[PDB]
Image 1 (cartoon, helix red, strand yellow):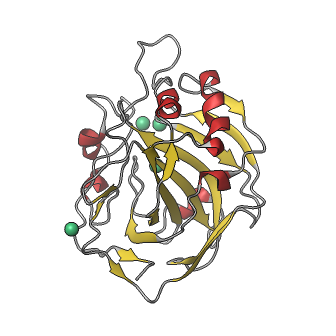
Image 2 (image 1 turned 90 degrees about the vertical axis):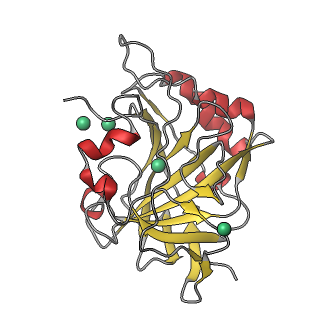
Length: 259
Ligand SMILES: [Zn+2]
Ligand SMILES: [Zn+2]
Ligand SMILES: [Zn+2]
Ligand SMILES: [Zn+2]
């Protein structure tokens, strides 16, 4: 029937009608309350190893845009922190708002940022992303907040290509992109067990949400909003507000990597 989305009839408040895990015990995103998040001395140092990352292409999937990487080798990986083993970078994408005052998925003390970046990784314990996403320890998503301020040079190559992938299904070559340019200086983070923030909402993600945002310009974020959810020849639906509301923490603890 109708595929899920972010619109009035197919968006987040309705996803449970087809994906009942939406009301599960380990759903994402959540509010991160800084007064109750607790330092966990058992966390090991976090290793973000992106020196050899090979980007390939950028795709408008009708929900967001994904920048895909070659994940055939243990090169662009995340290790340490809360993770056991090695997690390969497969793609990143963003969530953003119809205006700068909303857009992020996670919140910090109920505050929203203009957008949120997700760097998606899968556990090489499993054969590939499709096998990993079915497992509780399968995925690790590095979440980074975008705050409006000065323009980010590391984002400019992304925003420059978006007019070539305006509608669902369009893709373009996207090579030689350095995802380190989308990282803040500090890797202090919060972590908790959660889920994909889109259908099928599987509870297979270890979330690692960095405390320090990256700064982007209002003009850069506005370029995100010129994408469309629809395919060519369908009524125009601007790609905005492609975020899920925060969900109940339930019986989970958000841990901090910092004292
Ligand atoms: Zn569908
Ligand atoms: Zn609080
Ligand atoms: Zn889809
Ligand atoms: Zn995401």
